[PDB]
Amino acid sequence: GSSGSSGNDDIIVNWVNETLREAEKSSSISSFKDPKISTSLPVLDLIDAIQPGSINYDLLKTENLNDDEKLNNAKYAISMARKIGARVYALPEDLVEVNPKMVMTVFACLMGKGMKRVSGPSSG
């Protein structure tokens, strides 16, 4: 749930964690500059957590990845985004190096659901 202050930019991380927690995922992040992101674990699981059936670990690697594999993972993650409707403008090449320069549109776009507004003072 959006328990807290729905709006801040720090929620971009909390959400990712929660969303995965409620989904019972083994992926997560610590900050916009998280290492695990290199494997696209938190970025891949985050999507599935919302729409089960898209991400198929079967095709994924998530095992001793490398400059080569790591990439394929980045390209796949972004691919799904658009599939579900996450028109993003970034490159999987920079994502492999946990670069917040391109990821700025990665998570942000996904967080598009978080930020919101209501008429009455409702918490959630």
Image: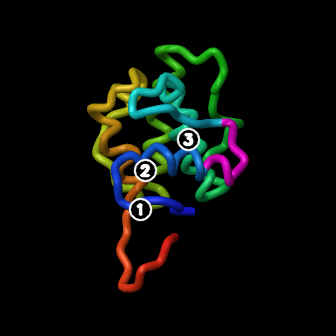
* Mark 2 and mark 1 residues within 8 Å of each other at the beta carbon: yes
- Disc 3 residue type (three-letter): Leu
| Residue under numbered circle 1 | 6
Query: In the rendered view, how is the structure colored?
Result: rainbow
Total residue callouts: 3
- Per the image, is 25 magenta? yes
Of labels 3 and 1, earlier in sequence is 1
Estimate the x, y position of residue 32 in percent, counting from the top left: 39, 33
- Disc 1 residue type (three-letter): Ser
Q: Nearer the viewer, residue 45 or 6?
A: 6
- Disc 2 residue type (three-letter): Ile
Of labels 3 and 2, earlier in sequence is 2
Give neighbour class at mark 1: few <14, some 14-19, many 20+ (Cα, 10 Å). some
Q: What residue range appears in magenta?
A: 20-26
**Tag 2's secondary structure?**
helix
- Per the image, is 54 magenta? no
| Residue under numbered circle 2 | 11
Estimate the x, y position of residue 8 in percent, counting from the top left: 35, 54
| Residue under numbered circle 3 | 44
Determine whether, in the image, residue 64 is placed left or right of residue 5. Answer: right
Estimate the x, y position of residue 38 in percent, counting from the top left: 48, 24
Question: Which label number is shown at residue 53?
Answer: none
